[PDB]
Length: 167
Ligand SMILES: [Ca+2]
Ligand SMILES: [Ca+2]
Image (cartoon, rainbow, N blue to C red):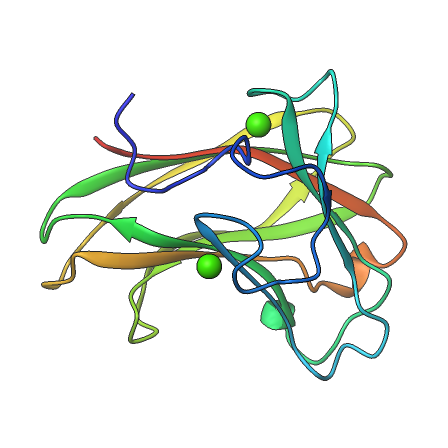
């Protein structure tokens, strides 16, 4: 496959809890804002029902901050071409009922190209997909996933298989 993003399924990363949030995971930038007093646990998990490969990323939300983006996992770099339309697809599920995630893509100047907004994540793996167009002249963009919804407190959200494909 040809994909714009790197390590979309976490398969390059050693299993374990991630403490180096910015650079612990190839292809991703994880971040927790200082308003999150009870920090989440980010973990690359080896599990037999990973949708892709052997690994997934697990995000255990123990608290939240002021905005959903105060807990986020961002695919970076995402290599694209001006004016091209892309398909975004990812798989997600949660440990418990009642999870919410927004899947977004934007540039380095914090212009958003598109998103799937407050998606309802269930206890079973589902695909989440949308299209977006690089409507400016950027070639290296980012794909922030927002986890910091109050509804997620006490839950673990799993993601796998991010693929951003030239449509
Ligand atoms: Ca995987
Ligand atoms: Ca990084």
